[PDB]
Image: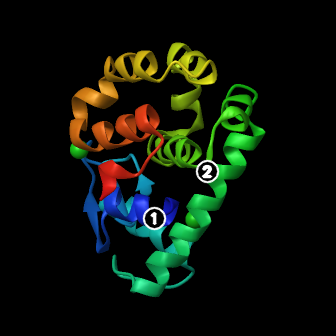
Amino acid sequence: MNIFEMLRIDEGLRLKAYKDTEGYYTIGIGHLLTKSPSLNAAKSELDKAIGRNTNGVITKDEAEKLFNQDVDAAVRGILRNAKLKPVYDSLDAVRRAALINMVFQMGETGVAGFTNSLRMLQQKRWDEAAVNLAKSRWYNQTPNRAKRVITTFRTGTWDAYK
Ligand SMILES: [Cl-]
Ligand SMILES: [Cl-]
């Protein structure tokens, strides 16, 4: 198991523009296209991202291509971020994967916001950080996924995913 596999399970794979759990236009493996309630705006972004006249649909290859880009941007975003980097640096491999997952989903800014949890993670207080993570809009809105990510942090294993 690895990050790609992990995120592929959490996000799914849709080749046709759909709306996310917050109603935003997304496509592929959780690739956000736009917040804007407009499908054309969606289609526009989409063609702009793929580089062709898509008509709201992409191929698997395409989908995977956006995913590679996004996973890469998420890692680099963490390593760039003053608040995240040290957390990341302090973590073992499995847990790093959990942090990347949160970053892929909510953005670096969103995550940089779990100040308290971050600190707990850095201090290796697993159970406490898990509890704290749960007190969030995130957990409340996407509780199942949130639980898998939270368990991964708590345990340092991939059990939540097997
Ligand atoms: Cl893009
Ligand atoms: Cl969920």
Q: Quadrant of residue 128?
A: top left
Q: Quarter holding the N terminus?
A: bottom left
**SS class of the residue under badge 2?**
helix
x, y (%) of residue 112? 59, 26
Q: Quarter holding the C terminus?
A: bottom left
55 and 120: which one is in front? Answer: 120
* Callout 2–callout 1 Cβ contact below 8 Å: no
Ligand 1's quadrant: bottom right
x, y (%) of residue 105? 44, 45
- C-alpha span from label 2 to label 1: 18 Å
For label 2, the crowd category at 10 Å Cα-Cα, with few meaning under 14, some 14 to 19 and many 20 or more, is many
Q: Amino acid at mark 2?
A: Ala
Which of the two labelled residues, at mark 2 and mark 1, occupies the earlier sequence position?
1
Q: Amino acid at mark 1?
A: Met
x, y (%) of residue 121? 56, 24
For disc 2, the marked residue is 74
- Number of residue marks: 2
**SS class of the residue under badge 1?**
loop
The colour scheme used to paint the residues is: rainbow
Which mark, residue 1? 1
Q: Quadrant of residue 82?
A: top right
Residue in the picture at 60% in, 16% down: 119
In front: mark 2 or mark 1? Answer: 1
Residue in the picture at 65% in, 55% down: 73
Q: Would residue 119 appear left or right of 57 to someone viewing this image?
A: right
Within 8 Å of ligand 2, the CB of disc 1?
Answer: no
150 relative to 135, above or below = below
